[PDB]
Amino acid sequence: SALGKLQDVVNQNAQALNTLVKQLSSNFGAISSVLNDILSRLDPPEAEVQIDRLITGRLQSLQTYVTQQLIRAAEIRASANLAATKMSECVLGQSKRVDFCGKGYHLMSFPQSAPHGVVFLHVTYVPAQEKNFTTAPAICHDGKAHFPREGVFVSNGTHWFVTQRNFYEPQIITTDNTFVSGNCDVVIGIVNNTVYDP
Amino acid sequence: TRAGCLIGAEHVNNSYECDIPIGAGICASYQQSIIAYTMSLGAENSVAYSNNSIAIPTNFTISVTTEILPVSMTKTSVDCTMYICG
Amino acid sequence: YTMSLGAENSVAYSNNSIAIPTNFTISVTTEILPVSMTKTSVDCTMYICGDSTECSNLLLQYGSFCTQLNRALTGIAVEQDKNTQEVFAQVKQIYKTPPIKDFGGFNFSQILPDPSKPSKRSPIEDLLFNKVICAQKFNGLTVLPPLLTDEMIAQYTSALLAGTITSGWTFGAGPALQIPFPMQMAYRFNGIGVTQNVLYENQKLIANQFNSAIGKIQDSLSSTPSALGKLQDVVNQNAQALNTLVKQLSSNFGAISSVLNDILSRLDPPEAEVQIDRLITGRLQSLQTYVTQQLIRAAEIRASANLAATKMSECVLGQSKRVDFCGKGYHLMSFPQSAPHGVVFLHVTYVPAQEKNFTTAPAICHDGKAHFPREGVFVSNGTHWFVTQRNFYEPQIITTDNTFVSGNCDVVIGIVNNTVYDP
Amino acid sequence: LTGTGVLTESNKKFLPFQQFGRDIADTTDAVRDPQTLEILDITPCSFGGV
Ligand SMILES: *[C@@H]1O[C@H](CO)[C@@H](O[C@@H]2O[C@H](CO)[C@@H](O)[C@H](O)[C@H]2NC(C)=O)[C@H](O)[C@H]1NC(C)=O
Ligand SMILES: *[C@@H]1O[C@H](CO)[C@@H](O[C@@H]2O[C@H](CO)[C@@H](O)[C@H](O)[C@H]2NC(C)=O)[C@H](O)[C@H]1NC(C)=O
Ligand SMILES: *[C@@H]1O[C@H](CO)[C@@H](O)[C@H](O)[C@H]1NC(C)=O
Ligand SMILES: *[C@@H]1O[C@H](CO)[C@@H](O)[C@H](O)[C@H]1NC(C)=O
Ligand SMILES: *[C@@H]1O[C@H](CO)[C@@H](O)[C@H](O)[C@H]1NC(C)=O
Ligand SMILES: *[C@@H]1O[C@H](CO)[C@@H](O)[C@H](O)[C@H]1NC(C)=O
Ligand SMILES: *[C@@H]1O[C@H](CO)[C@@H](O)[C@H](O)[C@H]1NC(C)=O
Ligand SMILES: *[C@@H]1O[C@H](CO)[C@@H](O)[C@H](O)[C@H]1NC(C)=O
Ligand SMILES: *[C@@H]1O[C@H](CO)[C@@H](O)[C@H](O)[C@H]1NC(C)=O
Ligand SMILES: *[C@@H]1O[C@H](CO)[C@@H](O)[C@H](O)[C@H]1NC(C)=O
Ligand SMILES: *[C@@H]1O[C@H](CO)[C@@H](O)[C@H](O)[C@H]1NC(C)=O
Ligand SMILES: *[C@@H]1O[C@H](CO)[C@@H](O)[C@H](O)[C@H]1NC(C)=O
């Protein structure tokens, strides 16, 4: 069922054609669904009446088919447009768009050809094995409020570190990985620690 | 049910992922006999939120998922005159 | 009158003048999208022939038209559940908020479920649902219930809200990683090129602007009946289509009567079939018109649902860089709210305010070297040069720690002389 | 006036001259009994998809 999306397209169109063909067996009120039987039995003055009924029915059947193909084609076009967009943004680049190139943080994608379609293999980064830390919005040192330049301030229960947000990597809090803005009397939840100066 | 009268399925209180949709929150599945149930929307997950607690990944996995999209459709051509009149 | 295109605004452009916001506001806007359409089902045979065997037998002469029509409407009905699922069922787990709503002053009571009501809707969702058959059924026109009930959709929405509030965007990528709300907002400030200290040093202001904006949403919707016109339009179009379809059963289409039973009670088969043929043709044509318009309309709804699903992913489960995709302003976050056959997004954006004029320069010349700002822009208050973050006036002393050197002073056009402080 | 359905006592305020009623679909949904002058509501016999 993995390729159901492509099989569904095949099935819908095959069904539409089969229906269209089967409509040629309908009388539509005529003495026969077979045009040759009408022509071999009746003279023109009467044959035309029977044929008119078949033409009306068969033209209506064909207009139904075409209308449904136009609507279905529009759906396929939209799908193709999406596929083209993903090719550009997932394969020819790295996308920031959430859930656009698979679940997780998109790294890259690889296209694979399929029958009347495309398959994208989305390679994503998925965070794992998280653990609890105590955190603070800022560190108070020498009366100054220090904020992390890239990461977040965390405590392992005794010591404060600064770490990149998506991967635990506890560095010593220093003036090279923080910046100062204002004093310690403004930030809510600010905690006291040392900020090391190299 | 709100979808109509369902006969031949055993209704149970146990909620499962939806298998065969009935309507109005009701789904049926084969478990043997056919059963009816209110579909689950997923497992409950209470996040350990606090004003000073953060969870940080110590590891990661590389996941590969497959997305399948239709691109093209069979290029049919129907001869109107022949179809109708042969 | 000739319509206005808006007020004229001449921007005070010059080759050395920049405007920088000294303040900001937190704006919340509402975006309303259709997701689903009423799942109608029309019994072709009954619509055309009722319970008449004579008509039914004549109808068979037309082949499988009724099978096609029943199939087309079935396909639409199924799509409608797919549309809803794509938009709302985006979360692996049902997340719940804490018993204690402490988010650093941020108040979500109007978007979170109200436990005092049986429906478990938020105050806003309740409002949305308040804002937005037999005669049809008796002719073979039935309505099928959505696979997901309104209570299930609300549960999906509340799960998304709980995830967003307690774990930010992490739950939309992998496991839900808890984070203090103020800290989450600080991350979202960084996401729009504003430093995190701007959040923390203005936390109460921001929480207050946010809380006020949310309150305004409820009032705006309540006092504006047309607010949900997009969803009402869908309801009206489909109701109109059904009403038209039903009324077509009163048409003679050239027959002696629009009532099939009257034809059958008056005429013998040889003549009744002629009159019935006229009704079948007219009623089949009426039904094919209905179905065709439902397929076209369904396609429009599908596109809307696809957009809604995209916004759910990119506006709610993450922070979007796409301009005007998640409201007007710099997107911070969004909160979904359930609506009748649709979804309402409350987009929270950062809007720059109270800008003021500064003199600017592309570079600072010091010791023969051209210094460029590492993150911000060089500005002068008329006497002294500072470097500031671009989206919020915060004039720092120009130092070697907030600039970088590239080449000499003889290349850059508009370079100005100043001191670059070395700590 | 022929048809198939379930007949019940009507609560419709028929005027003395009105012989039958119709719904928004413009189909007979009530009749006046030609002998008793009783007003009867007409609904279709229960049906639905299977
Ligand atoms: C930035 O704008 C906000 C309002 O959007 C200012 O806060 C208001 O200040 C006035 C006094 O001038 C108070 O009466 C209002 O109640 C405040 N509003 C809120 C929500 O607190 C804020 O002072 C401005 N900041 C700067 C630097 O101009
Ligand atoms: C969050 O905001 C709501 C209002 O939107 C607050 O609820 C109001 O509380 C006051 C009492 O302080 C009542 O008089 C109002 O009638 C309440 N309004 C509604 C709609 O309930 C709620 O208290 C706020 N939460 C916090 C923690 O401040
Ligand atoms: C964090 O602490 C909570 C209890 O407050 C616990 O349920 C949760 O599992 C912990 N997180 C991790 C990764 O252990
Ligand atoms: C925190 O980290 C420091 C440095 O690695 C270590 O010495 C200390 O014991 C750790 N504390 C806890 C509770 O693990
Ligand atoms: C968290 O809440 C507690 C009260 O439950 C309070 O004492 C503490 O200061 C708060 N911390 C922050 C960062 O808000
Ligand atoms: C931090 O230390 C200072 C003294 O240097 C003290 O006055 C202040 O209250 C402390 N703040 C906290 C949160 O411990
Ligand atoms: C389901 O729970 C109800 C009580 O609400 C009980 O009466 C019923 O028998 C239960 N059905 C099954 C299969 O357990
Ligand atoms: C900047 O100066 C122009 C005049 O050159 C003035 O029209 C404009 O309002 C000023 N900008 C601000 C924020 O005052
Ligand atoms: C520019 O800022 C400096 C430092 O705050 C101040 O001393 C100076 O007076 C300001 N100049 C003007 C025109 O405001
Ligand atoms: C701006 O234009 C003036 C002439 O109007 C010129 O003297 C000045 O050098 C220009 N400054 C820059 C940065 O181009
Ligand atoms: C900057 O100062 C140098 C002398 O150190 C001078 O030669 C140069 O012309 C000045 N440039 C400007 C724009 O004032
Ligand atoms: C005959 O019909 C009239 C109404 O037209 C009614 O009043 C009368 O009672 C009926 N008589 C009998 C025997 O049914």
Image (spheres, helix red, strand yellow):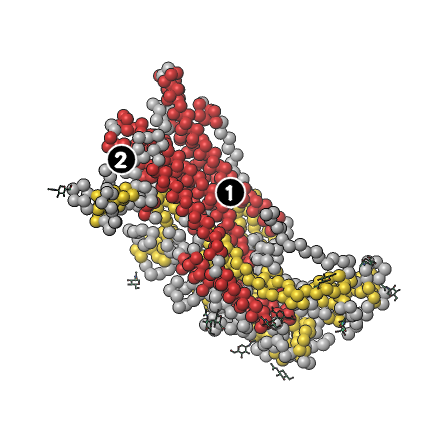
- Image height of C392 relative to A85, above or below: below
Q: Which residue is mark 2?
A: C261
Residue at 64% over, 64% down:
C353
Q: How far apart are labels 1 and 2 at the CA level?
A: 42 Å
Q: Is the distance from the Cβ of mark 2 to the nearest ligand 12 atom less than 8 Å?
A: no
Residue B81 place in picture, x, y as percent: 47, 24
Q: Secondary structure at mark 1?
A: helix
Q: Residue furthest top?
A: A43
Q: Chain of mark 2?
A: C
Callout 2 secondary element = helix
Label 1, on which residue?
Answer: A75
Q: Residues within 10 Å of mark 1 (few under 14, many from 20)?
A: some
Q: Between residues A35 and C125, which one lies in front from this camera angle?
A: C125
> Residue B84 in the image: x percent, y percent?
44, 25
Return the residue nearer the eye: B58 or C42.
Answer: C42
Residue at image point 32% right, 54% down: B1
Q: Amino acid at mark 2?
A: Asn
Left or right placement of residue A185 versus residue C313 in this view: right
